[PDB]
């Protein structure tokens, strides 16, 4: 897989293990209808906002190998949920090297860069 910069897609998080395929990478495919392609660093603001929008990332769901997130965790977000937060001015920082090029179908690279940690 490739990142938004054209390089090899780096791991987003190995602990907690993230990604739709739970291999730590924000890679996607047919079954990942949510397109978990944006590697972002969680902020309390985003976590609270996205829960208000019906996306609970704080409650653990072990049956989904989901631990419940905390500020500081890096996690592969659905492009749409990151986009929604960006329009609300609360999008969490992006790790470009761990963000799949597929993210470019939802967000412009310049917008991703403006929010990058890297
Ligand atoms: Br798939
Ligand atoms: Br998400």
Image (spheres, grey):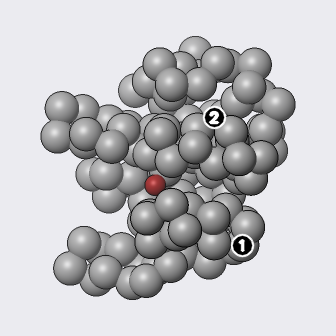
Q: Quadrant of residue 71?
A: bottom right
Cβ atoms at labels 1 and 2 below 8 Å apart? no
Judging from the image, what secondary structure is the residue with disc 2 in? helix
Q: Position of residue 49 (x, y in %)?
A: 63, 64
Closer mark to the observer between disc 1 and disc 2 = 1
Q: Secondary structure at mark 1?
A: helix
Work out which quarter of the rendered image holds the C terminus and state it. top right
Question: Which one is nearer the viewer's eye here, 72 or 58?
Answer: 58
Image position of 48 with respect to 62: above or below: above
Say which residue label 1 marks.
44
The disc placed on residue 94 is none
Give residue 86's position: percent from left, percent from top: 69, 41
> Where is residue 60 shown, x and y percent of the image?
39, 84
Report if residue 19 is visible in the image. yes
Q: Is residue 45 left or right of residue 75?
A: right
Q: Residue at x 25, y 42 (%)?
A: 32
Image position of 4 (left or right of 1):
right
Q: Residue 92: x and y, percent?
A: 71, 52
Query: Residue at the spot x=63%, y=34% of the render?
Result: 97
- Circle 2 residue: 97
């Amino acid at each position: 897989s490739q990142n938004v910069l054209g390089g090899v897609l780096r791991a987003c998080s190995m602990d907690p293990e993230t990604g739709f395929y739970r291999d730590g990478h924000c890679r996607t495919g047919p079954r990942d209808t949510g397109s978990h392609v944006v590697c972002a660093e969680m902020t309390e603001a985003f976590l609270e906002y996205t829960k208000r929008q019906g996306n609970d990332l704080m409650t653990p769901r072990p049956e989904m190998d989901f631990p419940g997130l905390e500020p500081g965790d890096r996690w592969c977000l659905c492009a749409a949920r990151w986009r929604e937060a960006m329009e609300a001015g609360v999008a969490p920082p992006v790790v470009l090297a761990a963000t799949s090029e597929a993210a470019l179908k939802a967000v412009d690279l310049e917008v991703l860069k403006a929010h990058a940690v890297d």
